[PDB]
Amino acid sequence: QTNQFSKYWKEVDMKIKGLLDKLNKSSDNVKKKIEALLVEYLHFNNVIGQ
């Protein structure tokens, strides 16, 4: 409704990079969890970019 796609896109990109940098700082058990969450955050960002 607002058409503020770029603001939310940058916000979600920051979220993505945060998850990526936290991926290497985490244990394997929760590493799997971070990777599984990345698979969906990237879908979010790709949809918003489209």
Image (cartoon, rainbow, N blue to C red):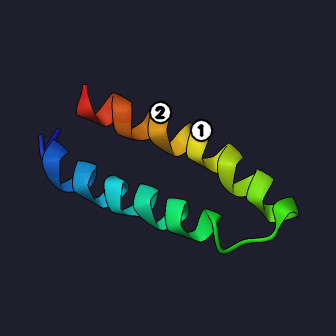
The residue that label 1 is drawn on is 39
Task: Specify the quadrant that holds the C terminus.
Answer: top left
State the CA–CA distance, disc 2 to disc 1: 7 Å
Quarter residue 7 falls in: bottom left
Say above or below: 24 vs 10. below
Q: Residue at x 42, y 60 (%)?
A: 17
Label 1 SS = helix
User: Number of marks in the image?
Assistant: 2
Q: Residues within 10 Å of mark 2 (few under 14, many from 20)?
A: few
Say above or below: 1 vs 50. below
Quarter residue 11 falls in: bottom left
Q: Position of residue 22 (x, y in %)?
A: 58, 70
Q: Is residue 49 left or right of residue 34?
A: left
Q: Position of residue 12 (x, y in %)?
A: 36, 54
- Type of amino acid under label 2: His
Residue sticking out furthest to the top = 50
Q: Is residue 44 left or right of residue 1?
A: right
Say above or below: 12 vs 18. above
The residue that label 2 is drawn on is 43
Q: Are marks 2 and 1 in contact (CB under 8 Å)?
A: yes
Say above or below: 44 vs 4. above
- Numbered mark located on residue 30 in the image: none
Q: Is residue 21 left or right of residue 14?
A: right
Q: Nearer the viewer, residue 25 or 38?
A: 25
- Type of amino acid under label 1: Val
Quarter residue 28 falls in: bottom right
